[PDB]
Image (cartoon, rainbow, N blue to C red; front, side, top):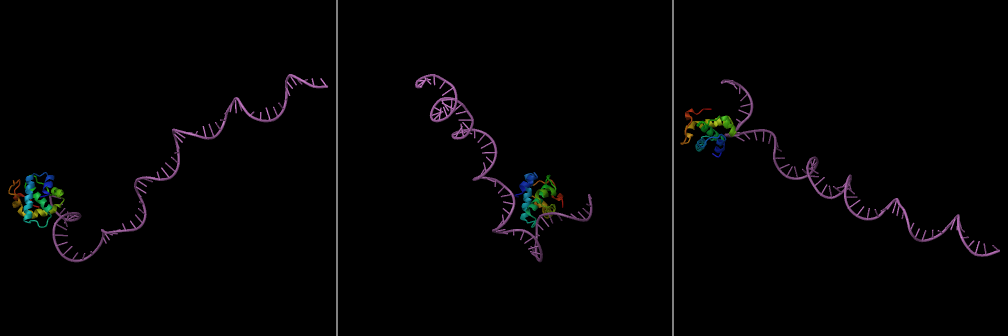
Amino acid sequence: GDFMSRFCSNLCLPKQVQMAATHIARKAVELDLVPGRSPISVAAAAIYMASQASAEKRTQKEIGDIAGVADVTIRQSYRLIYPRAPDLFPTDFKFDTPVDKLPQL
DNA sequence: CGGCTCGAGTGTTCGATCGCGACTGAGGACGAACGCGCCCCCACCCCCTTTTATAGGCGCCCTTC
């Protein structure tokens, strides 16, 4: 969450996406869904997922470029969080794309 | 066969010249104390390599669009 602020800022993402990502991240770590990947890598994928759950979608490479992590590392981290993509979202959220329609990579 | 009035030549201070040097200040050039920085040396301590085990990050290539 300490990096949710500036990165989402650097993407000019609205707080609701930013906050949604934070929950997604928070829920994921409490459940230890990703016992390996760096939390920033995990956070970026959450941000990605979040951005992919809003109109403010971005390509992994752009996100990857902002976070500095490898685009495959997000892709892997995404693969780890994707099984719970629907339930990881906060209860106070408004989809722009169904979790079913969340892309795979 | 005696006095007495020139002219000529020499010596000693003193008046009159007068060029030179001393005294003072300003200007110009050079030097020394002061000064700056680099280069050199000594001192102190890191750098490289391998093996075995793990795992997260990641770069490159091959293929397809």
